[PDB]
Amino acid sequence: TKVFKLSFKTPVHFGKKRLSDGEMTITADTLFSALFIETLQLGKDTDWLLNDLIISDTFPYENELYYLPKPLIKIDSNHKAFKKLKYVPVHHYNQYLNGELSAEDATDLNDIFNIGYFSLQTKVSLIAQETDSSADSEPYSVGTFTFEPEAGLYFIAKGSEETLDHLNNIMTALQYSGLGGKRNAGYGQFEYEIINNQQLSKLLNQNGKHSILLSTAMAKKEEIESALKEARYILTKRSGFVQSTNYSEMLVKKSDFYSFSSGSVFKNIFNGDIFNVGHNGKHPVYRYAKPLWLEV
Amino acid sequence: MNKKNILMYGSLLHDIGKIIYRSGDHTFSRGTHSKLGHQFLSQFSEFKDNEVLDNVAYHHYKELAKANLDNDNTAYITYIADNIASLFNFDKYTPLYSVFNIVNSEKLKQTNGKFKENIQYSSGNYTTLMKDMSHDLEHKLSIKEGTFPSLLQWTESLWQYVPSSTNKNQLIDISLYDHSRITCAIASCIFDYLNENNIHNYKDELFSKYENTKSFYQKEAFLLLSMDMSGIQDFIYNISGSKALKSLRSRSFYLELMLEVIVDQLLERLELARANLLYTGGGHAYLLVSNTDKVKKKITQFNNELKKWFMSEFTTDLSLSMAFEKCSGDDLMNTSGNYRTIWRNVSSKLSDIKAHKYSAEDILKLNHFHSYGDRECKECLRSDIDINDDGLCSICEGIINISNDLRDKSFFVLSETGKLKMPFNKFISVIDYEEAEMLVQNNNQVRIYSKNKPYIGIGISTNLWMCDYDYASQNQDMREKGIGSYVDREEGVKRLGVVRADIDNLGATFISGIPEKYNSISRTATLSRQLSLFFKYELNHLLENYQITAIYSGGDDLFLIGAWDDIIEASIYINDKFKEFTLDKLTLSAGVGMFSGKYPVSKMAFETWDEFKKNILEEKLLVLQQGFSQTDEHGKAFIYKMLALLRNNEAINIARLAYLLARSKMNEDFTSKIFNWAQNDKDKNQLITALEYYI
Amino acid sequence: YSKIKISGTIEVVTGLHIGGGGSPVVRDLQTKLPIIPGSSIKGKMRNLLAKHFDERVLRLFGSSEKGNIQRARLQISDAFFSEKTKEHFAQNDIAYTETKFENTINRLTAVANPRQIERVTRGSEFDFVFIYNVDEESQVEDDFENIEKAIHLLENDYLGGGGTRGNGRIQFKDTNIETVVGEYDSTNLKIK
Ligand SMILES: Nc1ncnc2c1ncn2[C@@H]1O[C@H](COP(=O)(O)OP(=O)(O)OP(=O)(O)O)[C@@H](O)[C@H]1O
Ligand SMILES: Nc1ncnc2c1ncn2[C@@H]1O[C@H](COP(=O)(O)OP(=O)(O)OP(=O)(O)O)[C@@H](O)[C@H]1O
């Protein structure tokens, strides 16, 4: 059960709805999609790394601090300072889960959370009749994020040792491809390092009664009724197009899929499944929904 | 008349006699308020209903002692209601005090201000108001089942600054309109609770013995209800098209009117009056309703229908959550500060029943609909909705229609055909006042929602408050123009300004409020009304001399967009004018940025005092502007070399800047002041900001 | 399946102006050092290599908008000041950007209206990385011939704005080609 640390050194576009949108972290959907596409480009075998690997979402880091999302847990006291907060570092996470975090501490933690800044870079497209005759340029915009020299994102993955060796090989392949949007236009390369942090391991290997969903999951048909007994959760319409399925890219677009967010809390665990969002295509297109649980 | 309507029409006029006694020129019965009000109402044909007269004439203990009324007579509920809403020398000239002083007076008690320094009212004013209300009462008011909202509106129009109780020993901050409204609300709630819970001889249920009376205060006969729009931000700020100005003023308004129609329709279901609405704005609404099984069953069913609708069009972008909590009338009289406990409890229940939003079968249905769909509206960043011509769906085009129709027409109508799609199988179209009338005698089941216009008195006249201002119509062409219509200003760079503001101390103010002594339902209600009316009229007036169009304003959110210079000037003006109205008790935090024209406005929104006014704008900016005005040839080149020296904070650069200023031809005073400022860090940052503003 | 890496450094022979701000030049919003975007390299290279002649243009950069879909086979990244240029300019105390004053002459009037255009300093060096995803073994020679001819053209052309007016001339030095994925040899491929 190793974790991967990602350093970029080139600004990245990650996207939610429009190319001028900017997002900091991405979900296991896009990550698993990227690993799948690089496995196919390598021409390796896909069965091994389809139904054995569990991936958590991306989570940012700073110099020596690692971050996990806020559990949507019901704290009984402001209801303001906690709302403006998204992420809680590993040092104070058990403190948060047990009410040992104070409002001034919330303000301080928010104050220290400078881990990147946003930007819109302008661009123009002169493939149009500006080649031919008097015709206006068509400026467009892209949304980017840049990390300070000691920031990045990290993963948490688990599985058999063989699965993790394969994951290492594919990640080596991927570091020179991208992990974002306009990869081919100069955004989103990275170098990765595998480090074993004692504290994160301790946090991952507890035992409790609740569960904090660290990835984006959706229970299968026959478990959802007992899965949703007592829970606090946010759903997100996850959409997007597909790469090399049919003739027209504009005509091909995955059916919308809803999954629980990366902070939901549950009583009864559910295993997930890799769900097809496929139709009118030549090959199946996969979306990822399998949880990585944090048990406390 | 229905007995509930009898409670309504009687209660809202229980303390009417006060305005009559305080008049002095109308004191026919100089004995008590009750008898005088009874005599006054007793000349008019429409309000010639008798039980209403009894209600008004008997609103107090002593009078009721001998009226020999039935064990069921509506006035008794009026008595308990006035007590709930609530040595006694009433000075007719007592000036009303603004609640905003008392709020943060605990820390800093300032000289109690007052409405119209040491102002005082005068006798003839009340006589004039008597004339006015007799005029309206002969010519505008009429008694039918459905005119109660109209009566409430006229009370609102006439009374909002006539002091309710003028007791010299009490902190006078309640308008008589507030007292009357909350009394009517409480009366309605009591009537439903008693009628439902199988009690009929109310004289014996309540009045008989103070111990039994005190029990009734203790019984949990009231429910407080809450509302919350879930997905405000992502619905309002998903725009990329060329009609950015036109849509936003219309999308914001469509969401607002959605909230209003939801709350009105709910009130219609529960057979309650518009008085029971205590606060609307943003996404929240608070309702005070009856604590019966019937009401709760209806609430559950209505929540079901609403959630099914909102899934049937949006599925994540907008959802509504409601929650209610039992509360006892003893808690409304600020007995143990427990009002604050119950209010926080209902807030927590809302914030924790927004967690579990969708049932199992619901989330299955969301995921298993393989449907032939087209793609994302250029104007409205949404895929699920079904586009048409120009890559736009029907909803976005209806929004564009209402956008075009906003500027010239004022009345808004809820009907079966309309243009835009409303929750419970309704639609909205747009009309004019003559057209509104024509619909009125047509007796169509209509509601009129207006553009901050009273003196309507037309059908269901519902003066809904929304700040619609746009300098873009002050040009030679009255038609609404694009976002470039402010970009093209030549007095500076051709850029846009956007301003966002939040009240810093607003969570505490609605929750904590004034400690330990003014924490009733009445006093927090009047504070709510004051803030609401401030953000829904005062902005409209304050923004007049400014080239700004008002986008979304209300609650505690201030979202204005316009020309760069104008946004700064208007922001300063608004901050000062607010500090005036809140008597320097509440503070505002605001951000203004420079955004280029033709950016997707969805993206500029996600980007976004005494010190700035006195030190930067007033002194440094003025001397700098005079300096450049006196000496020509100081183009952007000279200023930008000044920047080049300044931003690199080095002493060799200070010498270089000295050389540059020496080579300029400014007066010795200007150069000397600039150099002295340049030697100091705080001053030089301020100087940088000021000269940047010059450009 | 191998990935070929084309790395090197480019010198600004005459001042450079990408100017996404306009008339500022593109920078990084924290480091405040100028950059040269990958989009600029790719766009100018594509325009040149296409005007030189098509299927090869589709091959190298990938269009996938004409009823058939081709995945990009050359990935171009941004460039940044090297440590060497930074240290040299610091020691000799040279600012990173020059500002040229310009002017325009009206006809029948002969009044001059001046402008102010910012320009990257001569001698600055940018470090770049390209990637070649060799999806077909039997075409790497042809594709590096094409990229050779493209770089040769860019050597004799300009990047950014105002090149007809005398700026943007660049140079390419210190190019090395290494194979970083797979087992394909690259000790014979050549780029100036
Ligand atoms: N039409 C509107 N346009 C812009 N801002 C609005 C509009 N209506 C309300 N707002 C403001 O936007 C704020 C943010 O709304 P938001 O989307 O956060 O919803 P919310 O009610 O706070 O729910 P949640 O807790 O789920 O965020 C509201 O508190 C309100 O002040
Ligand atoms: N007059 C009012 N009465 C009650 N609640 C109000 C009123 N005006 C605004 N609100 C509340 O304020 C919310 C807006 O939240 P927003 O994030 O804009 O600021 P806030 O959290 O209230 O302010 P702050 O954190 O500075 O105290 C609304 O959703 C609503 O619940």
Image (cartoon, coloured by chain):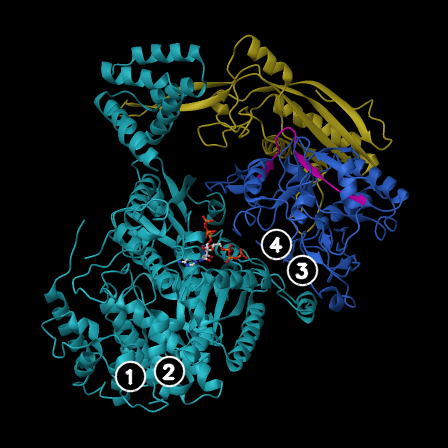
Q: Percent position (x, y) of residue A35?
A: 78, 45
**Spatial distance from mark 3 to mark 2, Cα to Cα?**
58 Å
Report crowding for label 1: few under 14, some 14 to 19, many 20 or more residues within 10 A (C-alpha).
some
Relative vertical location of residue B335 with respect to residue B620 in this rendering, above or below: below
| Pointers 2 and 1 in contact (C-beta within 8 Å) | yes
Q: Would you call the spot at circle 2 few (<14 residues within 10 Å), some (14-19), or many (20 or more)?
A: many
Left or right: A93 in relation to B192: right
Tag 1 residue: B64
Q: Are marks 3 and 4 on the same chain?
A: yes
Which colour denotes chain C? yellow
Residue closest to the eye, C23 or B464: B464
The answer to whether one can see residue B82 in this image is: yes
Q: Quadrant of the N terminus of chain B?
A: bottom left
Q: What residue is disc 4 on?
A: A75
Check disc 3 and give the amino acid type.
Tyr
Q: Which residues are magenta?
A: A144-157
Residue B162 in the image: state x and y as whole percent: 22, 65
Amino acid found under the numbered disc labelled 4: Ile
Chain of the residue that carries numbered disc 2 in the rendered image? B
Three-letter code for the amino acid on which mark 1 is drawn: Leu
Quickly name the residue at label 3. Answer: A258
